[PDB]
Amino acid sequence: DVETCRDERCYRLWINSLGIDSYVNNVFEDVRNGWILLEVLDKVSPSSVNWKHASKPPIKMPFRKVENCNQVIKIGKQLKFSLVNVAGNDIVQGNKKLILGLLWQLMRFHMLQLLKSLRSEMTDADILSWANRKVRTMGRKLQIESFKDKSLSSGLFFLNLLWAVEPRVVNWNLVTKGETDDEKRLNATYIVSVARKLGCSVFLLPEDIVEVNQKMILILTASIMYWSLQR
Amino acid sequence: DVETCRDERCYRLWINSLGIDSYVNNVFEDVRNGWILLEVLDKVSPSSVNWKHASKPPIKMPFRKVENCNQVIKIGKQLKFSLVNVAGNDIVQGNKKLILGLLWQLMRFHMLQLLKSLRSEMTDADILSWANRKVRTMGRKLQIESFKDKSLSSGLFFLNLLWAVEPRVVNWNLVTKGETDDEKRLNATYIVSVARKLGCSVFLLPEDIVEVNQKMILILTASIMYWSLQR
Amino acid sequence: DDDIAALVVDNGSGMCKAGFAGDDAPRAVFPSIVGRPRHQGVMVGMGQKDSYVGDEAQSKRGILTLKYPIEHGIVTNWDDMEKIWHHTFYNELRVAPEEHPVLLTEAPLNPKANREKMTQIMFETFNTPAMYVAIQAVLSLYASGRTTGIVMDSGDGVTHTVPIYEGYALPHAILRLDLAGRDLTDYLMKILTERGYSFTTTAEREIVRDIKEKLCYVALDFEQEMATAASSSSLEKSYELPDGQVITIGNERFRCPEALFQPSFLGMESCGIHETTFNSIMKCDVDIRKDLYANTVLSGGTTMYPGIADRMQKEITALAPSTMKIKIIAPPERKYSVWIGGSILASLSTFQQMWISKQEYDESGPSIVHRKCF
Amino acid sequence: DDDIAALVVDNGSGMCKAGFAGDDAPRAVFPSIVGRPRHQGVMVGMGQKDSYVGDEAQSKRGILTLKYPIEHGIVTNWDDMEKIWHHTFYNELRVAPEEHPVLLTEAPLNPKANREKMTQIMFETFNTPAMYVAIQAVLSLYASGRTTGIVMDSGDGVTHTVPIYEGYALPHAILRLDLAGRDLTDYLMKILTERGYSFTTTAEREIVRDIKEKLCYVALDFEQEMATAASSSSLEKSYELPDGQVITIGNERFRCPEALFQPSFLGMESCGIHETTFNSIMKCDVDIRKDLYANTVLSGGTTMYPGIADRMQKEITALAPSTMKIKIIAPPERKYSVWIGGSILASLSTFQQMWISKQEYDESGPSIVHRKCF
Amino acid sequence: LMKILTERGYSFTTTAEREIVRDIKEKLCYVALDFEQEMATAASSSSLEKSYELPDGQVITIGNERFRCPEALFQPSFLGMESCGIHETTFNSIMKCDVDIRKDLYANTVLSGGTTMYPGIADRMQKEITALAPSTMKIKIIAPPERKYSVWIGGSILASLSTFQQMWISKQEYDESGPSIVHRKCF
């Protein structure tokens, strides 16, 4: 049941970096009136939400809460997500199992869509290719086979990629080896701050790099790419 | 059934002198997960093993054990060895009759290959010729007709050959006559240590000389030769 | 590395476990039971959804009819199994079927046309790049300790006796019995309702499943056990309804699993389970039989009954030649073996030359499952 | 000294023994029986191997058809004998055929074309520097006590009566009978199955071989022995199946070896063994016959039956002139003689001028075996 | 037949209908000349599937099964049996006979019994004995179309001749010998 606490942090940080107008202090609580989830849906799938049938908080009337959550479920099923034996009132009641399931699929959906936009039709693979190729231009040979690659935990790859993008934002005297859990933790926190220094609006936690959360890895990299292609 | 105990010692000592990364405490047990046998195969027949399809110990999953042993059998049959009505799981189950048979052929295969490399195409005979000729340069007349020669048990030939190679490593006051089983045992143990003192990475047992194990005799001599030709 | 990796889908009578090859545990484990309304349903806070799966079907069990879709291991309802799979990909793993090969598991002795209908659906309805169908007991073995033997596999929808020589099932001597866990939940409820009991409300049709699994027993001697029901004192046990009410069960507890040994109790002409192990053994090579008696392994939820190892032993010992060493094996974990054996298997580069591809399915049709999956 | 030394290969109906000339005992003794699938087989944890040899064919005997390749001493299956030999060199002795001469042994009275096919294979298929084929009984003698006599040799695939004058077989008076141990295992199973018995599974086709060898007997007077089967009490003995089951054998035990004396029992027009010793003796030099009756020696596995010395004596005593001293000899070791006689022989420097060389085989062809191997 | 039909997910679940495979077998089975080119002349379907009607009202459809059933006679591996098929066993009895009647036994191969009634069995028996037989034998397989009461009226003739009363095994003889005597007197 400790995974519930980790997912709570993960999706909370992700939602707060999407450019949403609401701020999440606790995903399990702040998501119950359905508004935030509608916002995330509108961001990950533009124009998907019909705001004419939604109610903006604060909300006292329970009807307005159930209505928001039902649109959330509808759009979710329309996107081919997997929601069985649930409805809007499940979100209002705080069904954590459903909330985490809906959030995961939202995160995965956004990631795939981002990759797909790189096509011609972006894909996760195009992002993986860009990162490896970008590092090779600096003369370095370290590469990754995927965004799940275990070696990522060291943080060395990201720092090299960031250095490749803009060498002026990475001070190597400050970087450590990715060996001890402490050393990794240190680079991770450094990576997250340097990326934001470049313009990356990411919300993963330092431990998302140390534990190699592939979904969060994909988005960070894609975000680095985003700003690199505009330099 | 006492020959099983002797072979266990013999191949155990041989495997541990091949330069393998694993150490064998008991051939019948330590060979069951297939790893060691793959190592011996890679040494006796370079590049023969495909490590991309092998699993390095410790191994818990039985599938990985059976897979290693099946490659062992495959490469064995490819080398024209004789393996009938057996497969990888026979090694995993500890089939001692198969394990000893596979080991013998491995030992004989390596010996022939070594001799063959002396050609131009080395052969066992070229090694036999070198040893006899090397001793004749010191003025001694003792020779051998083969590596199975009964007179070898005395240990006098080896000590003369070693003395021929480097007189400084053989103290004759310490050598005995090769008559009593005790006297032979004493020279044998002396021979094994002096050879290692020169650089010979051999793994035969002192009794391998007293009982004249021709396969082990061949390798010791070839090893003496190896280092003699580099002096 | 994650996006790309086959999805292993293990289809159990009570539970489904689905994940990604190369992984240590199932990412989605869920209730199958599968429950279809048996009266056009749907709450207006759900799509016209007429298969509820897992726990959202526990909480309408009373208003729904529940299959364990899958029943005695075999699929009885094909559009509600189609629902389950759609939910596996699109809601639980959040995956796209047309980019991942699937390894689906199946019951020992699964009917011909079933193997073909799941090849059919998977290819045409989910447009799967490739697929394979492995028997569940064989992935339990790969994930672990034996290679020759005969397994007696009793799930929810079927039972089979399979003789295996060196990791290879011998298809001529495989025998299928269509009597497994669902047949026994059903027969329990009828003998309990015959005692004037009332399992009248949906959820409580699933309440016989827990009496069955909680109180049933296999008797060594049914006959001296029935009069060691009449010398009562210690045989009746009680079960409590959600309703507050009480159940008392006595001769029923051992009379339920007895339909496995005597399917006349069920109104079936079939031999029981003890004769079918013996009749597969007689169909095999004369020189492995002695191996098959020494290695009789039981696997599946319906083999979990107290007394079944002893009673299987007692009974095979009576039919077997007067000398055979008979060793019935009943490993106490007989919970995730089938799924991690498939996760191992579908991750080896070995396996990609083992699937039935989209190309092959076109080439052959649905029949090809029989050729390639043994 | 080891690497170089001929390899002696003794090819028995039940057992093969192979080693190096100059050695005291066989280094590899293995099961021949040779068992070929008689249904395209192979486990996928073996090559397409369709001759299993020795004990890895005992444990599939039930699923395989077993030749003893070699049968009554004679090779009935040539690619499965080719398999055995490949395994002798490449897996058992771990040798290279093109560097060692081979002494192969052969049955007394071995058919012409057989001698040539084993010359053929050995030279073209294994590229043997040289080879010789010696009769097995003659290497039994060299390894030991007689020089003039007639041997009656009964293996698995043939029987011959050979008159020998001073260490030299007299080829005109040699007579071959194609009825030996396999003919008798086969006829036993049919008279046992005629009694409504069931030897239905592979291994158990090899279970008649042990009844045959364990319970058969040769009767002195078949006729008074058959009614000393009807005065039963002590004649039926029992055999236990692997299956636990029981066999009971009675008149069959002596009725099996009787096909040697009366091959009408087998449906063969041939004289029995007692007449063939007598008809070779009549074909020899008038002045050694008295020597050949005084030295009738039996050799081979099929001569091991209780009563065969006495019944051979009784019968040769009836055909022989009313004065001949007839001494039938049946040494109780009639286990490694053939192999150590060949190991002695192929180690003498004498022998290298005795082989058929690669050169000669080219020169002549396969026929040369008839010239040089007597 | 019932196992290959039930393997196709069919259901012969009720007693009488275990005897309903006997009529499909006898009504639709066929012996193939070349099993191999016949199986792909099941995949070029159109004309091979035929239907059978249950008492229950229900329908059966049978295709490759019809010829795959009698094929177990020629290849008993289909049944899981090590036995030679029927074509080899005629040939191995012929080889066990007197050298001077064999030519007579190939010219007079007669089939008899209910299981010889399959369409194609005369031709396929001929084709197969013609492959094992020396390259010259005239092989004449005989398959009289009445192969219904012959066995009974042959016995009625025989047991009425005064000839026959010296041919029986009497109560006396049975006592004398036991049950074994049947082997002596009935050939």
Image (spheres, coloured by chain):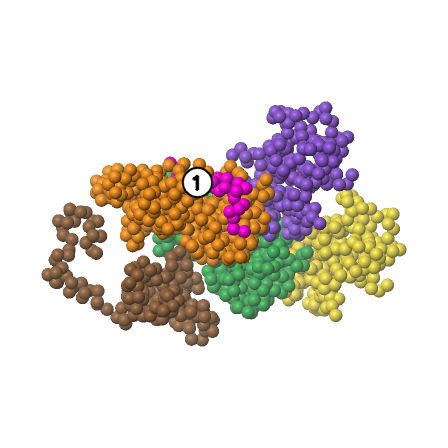
Chain colours: A yellow, B purple, C green, D orange, E brown
Tell me, yes or no, if residue A91 can be seen here. no
Q: Secondary structure at mark 1?
A: helix
x, y percentage for residue B80?
Answer: 58, 51
Q: Nearer the viewer, residue A19 or E60?
A: E60
Q: Residue furthest left?
A: E162
Chain of residue at mark 1: D
Residue at 73%, 66% in the rendered image: A122
Specify the segment rendered in magenta: D332-357
Residue D341 sits inside the magenta stretch: yes
Residue D333 sits inside the magenta stretch: yes
Residue at 37%, 45% in the rendered image: D163
Q: Quadrant of the C terminus of chain B?
A: top right
C311 over C358 or under it: above or below: above
Q: Residue furthest bottom?
A: E46
x, y percentage for residue D313?
Answer: 29, 40
Residue at 58%, 68% in the rendered image: C359
Q: Nearer the viewer, residue B124 or D301?
A: B124
B138 over D160 or under it: above or below: above
Residue at 45%, 72% in the rendered image: E41
Tell me, yes or no, if residue E161 can be seen here. yes
x, y percentage for residue B213?
Answer: 61, 36
x, y percentage for residue C19?
Answer: 61, 55
Q: Residue furthest right?
A: A168
Residue wearing tag 1 = D140
D312 over A16 or under it: above or below: above
